[PDB]
């Protein structure tokens, strides 16, 4: 499906695609290129816990194409500014990184991981990722003007900021195209309403408008600790819908096609609190698993991975356990073992990857939402090889096409 940026998954992956694995480890940045040779390559002696002083609680580390050549660069929101290591095209990156803007940082603009959100996104159809932050006064953007030149930060909209009452412990903020013009709009699950703000394509967003009185902490009792929510295309028209894992199960509100939204319906009595799903034990994702290229539901539960396939119209088929692994009963832990649903094979049907206690493992989609056997990738980038979730960042990312 289509480009959505969320707090949980700030580095989108392509469908179809052959995603790479990237690790910000103790010693710097390491990649596992998706290829016939599976190996770890150290590419930058920076952006690491010891190699550079990078901290999850102070800094943000992402991958984004900042030049327009469809190669992803490493972008870090560091201590005193934004630092970028560009992709050299050959599984190497520039080192040291370049400081492109003294803003959006812990000691340049007072940015705080616990109050603010920092993304990279092509907001103006230039082919290059601009810097986008949900800061104190609103949403701020720094335009990527090319050749590493980022312009001084401009206020894009005086909303969705900490000053307006937006809180990471209560609310959710996304970027997603809800209108179909290819521009990423803001979607914010506020106190009482889901709000959208249309991207005008010029570095600003239009005034926020409420679309749904549900999916929020004050409207339906949706909490961060218990009820995950996503935005995703559930019908194939490339416009994002709203999906939440609530108490009884999965609730949706479908986009009418113009950024207006339908009623909230319970579409599947599974994957919710009443079926025993718990944010601290389980992982719940929406990704395309089939040739319909719509959002299907994937849950890493107790006994393994469970999937319900979208019929193509936002209704769902039966829940099936597709692999007896990657689950809580197999020792997988949200606090220790990152798990992703991403295309690793290029067929457009997302696959599973997880960074286990000892090894990285994958399980490949057969093409129809059913899965093959578990496969070992490599014995690195794991707990026992010195990667603790709290001192490292790991992503699936398309470094190259
Ligand atoms: Ca749009
Ligand atoms: Ca695949
Ligand atoms: Cl710095």
Image: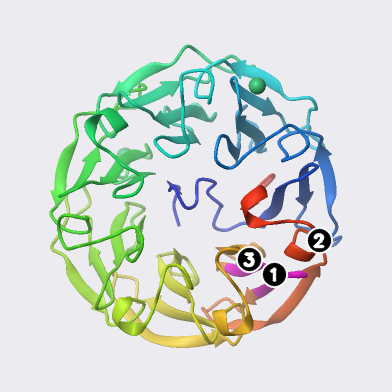
For ligand 1, give the image quadrant.
Answer: top left
From mark 1 to mark 2, how far is it between C-alphas? 10 Å
Tell me if label 3 and label 1 are in contact, CB under 8 Å. Answer: yes
Snapshot quadrant of residue 366: bottom right
Q: Is residue 125 visible?
A: no
Q: Determine whether the residue tagged by mark 2 lies in a helix, strand or loop.
A: helix
Q: Determine whether the residue tagged by mark 3 lies in a helix, strand or loop.
A: loop
Tell me if label 3 and label 2 are in contact, CB under 8 Å. Answer: no
The answer to whether residue 385 is above or below residue 189 is below
Frontmost residue, 55 versus 98? 55
Q: Determine whether the residue tagged by mark 1 lies in a helix, strand or loop.
A: loop
From mark 3 to mark 2, how far is it between C-alphas? 13 Å
The answer to whether residue 271 is above or below residue 189 is below
Q: Residue drawn 80% across and 42% down?
A: 27
Q: Which residue is mark 1?
A: 356
**Is 295 on the left or on the right of 16, as rendered?**
left
Q: Which residue is mark 2?
A: 385
| Dot placed on the residue nearer the N-terminal end, 3 or 2 | 3
């Amino acid at each position: 499906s289509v480009v959505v940026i969320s707090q949980a998954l700030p580095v989108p992956t392509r469908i179809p695609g052959v995603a790479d694995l990237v690790g910000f480890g103790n010693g710097g940045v390491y990649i596992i290129r998706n290829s016939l040779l599976i190996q770890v390559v150290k590419v930058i002696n920076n952006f690491g816990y010891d190699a550079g002083g990078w901290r999850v609680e102070k800094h943000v580390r992402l991958l984004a194409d900042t030049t327009g050549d469809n190669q992803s660069d490493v972008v870090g929101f560091g201590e005193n500014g934004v630092w970028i290591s560009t992709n050299n095209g050959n599984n190497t990156f520039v080192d040291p990184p370049k400081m492109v803007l003294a803003n959006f940082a812990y000691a340049a603009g007072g940015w705080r991981v616990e109050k603010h959100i920092r993304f990279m996104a092509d907001l103006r159809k230039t082919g290059r990722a601009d810097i986008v932050g949900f800061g104190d006064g609103g949403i701020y953007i720094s335009r990527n003007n090319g050749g590493g030149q980022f312009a001084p930060a401009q206020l894009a909209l005086n909303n969705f900021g900490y000053a307006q009452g937006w809180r990471l412990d209560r609310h959710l903020r996304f970027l997603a195209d809800v209108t179909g013009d290819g521009l990423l709009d803001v979607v914010g699950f506020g106190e009482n309403q889901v709000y959208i703000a249309r991207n005008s394509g010029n570095g600003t967003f239009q005034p926020a408008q409420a679309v749904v009185n549900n999916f929020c902490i004050g409207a339906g009792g949706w909490t961060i600790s218990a009820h995950p929510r996503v935005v995703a295309d559930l019908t194939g028209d490339r416009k994002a819908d709203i999906l939440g894992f609530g108490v009884a199960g999965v609730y949706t509100s479908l986009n009418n096609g113009n950024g207006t939204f339908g009623a909230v319906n319970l579409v599947l009595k599974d994957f919710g609190v009443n079926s025993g799903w718990r944010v601290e034990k389980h992982v719940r994702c929406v990704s395309s698993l089939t040739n319909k290229k719509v959002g299907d539901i994937i849950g890493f539960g107790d006994a393994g991975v469970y999937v319900a396939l979208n019929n193509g119209n936002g209704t769902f088929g039966p829940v099936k356990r597709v692999i007896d692994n990657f689950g809580y009963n197999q020792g997988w832990r949200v606090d220790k073992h990152p798990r992703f649903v991403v295309d690793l094979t290029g067929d457009g049907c997302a696959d599973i990857v997880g960074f286990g206690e000892n090894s990285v493992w994958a399980c490949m989609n057969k093409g129809d939402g059913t899965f093959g056997p578990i496969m070992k990738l490599i014995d690195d980038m794991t707990v026992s090889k010195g990667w603790t979730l709290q001192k490292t960042v790991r992503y699936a990312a398309n470094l190259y096409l």
